[PDB]
Image 1 (cartoon, rainbow, N blue to C red):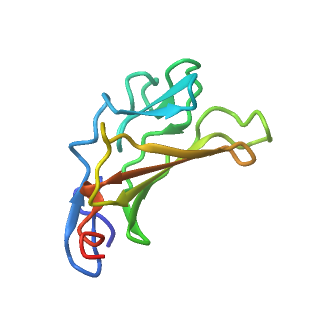
Image 2 (cartoon, rainbow, N blue to C red):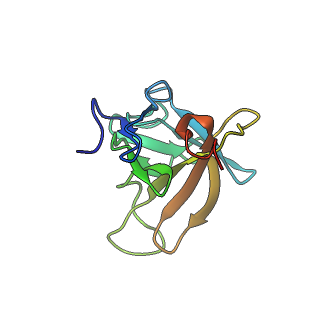
Image 3 (cartoon, one colour):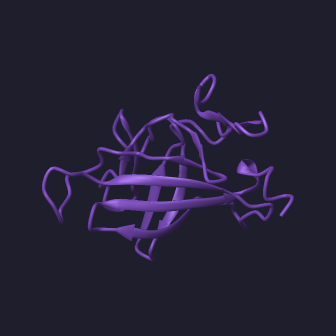
Length: 143
């Protein structure tokens, strides 16, 4: 179970598939890392601002914040990707940055419809992203 052709996950409760493959690709998307940075991260695949294998990095610093992973999973009405094995943890040892792309079912879209960085986790090198998009929605359309 979990996914189909990958990069796409199903409501296990509805049997409805979500595909973020139109979001996928080495083009990737961007998130605003504070006012100084931008994140460049591709969905499921590697990002072109990143070296082959890295699916998420910064635009200014080019510190990889995660590697390409196509495991889109339905979790708490969210669909979340996690791009691990980013750049070595400056704040710890033997760890790396990772992403948490929590796609959020929101019938309301973004102005641009960006993956919105919630916040950083420097304690365990996590970048918590949440993309409130009608793409991952179907459920919240109700409530």
